[PDB]
Image (cartoon, rainbow, N blue to C red; front, side, top):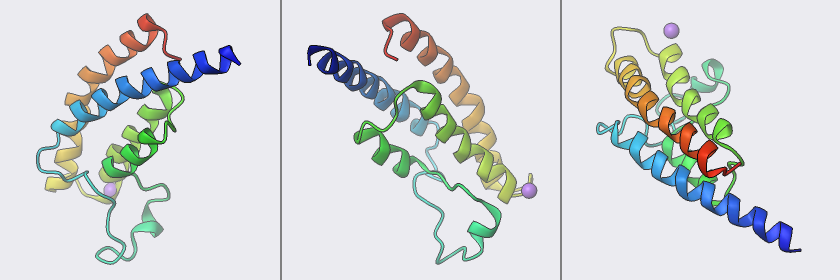
Length: 123
Ligand code: NA
């Protein structure tokens, strides 16, 4: 149908916007602490602590499959990256501190992203 095509165009445009958002968020992690999944070889007990692991590479996979239907779903995954890190790691670690900085700097980006999604009407 023409409607389904229109819906798919909207999703494709959302995916384009979120790809820009993802790139901006990841630029706020130049240490690449959050770039890849935590290794279960190097941290074998990780899943005892963290029930829903997340990282930028896993987000990018979902994004390119157009698996984010709205900005809320994308934000949920970003918050998982931050929140998982701040539970597993103590306050005095480079990991926890990187997550705080990413959260703070990311908030700016996500604030305007919400406005753009609402304005352009992409969801
Ligand atoms: Na903790």
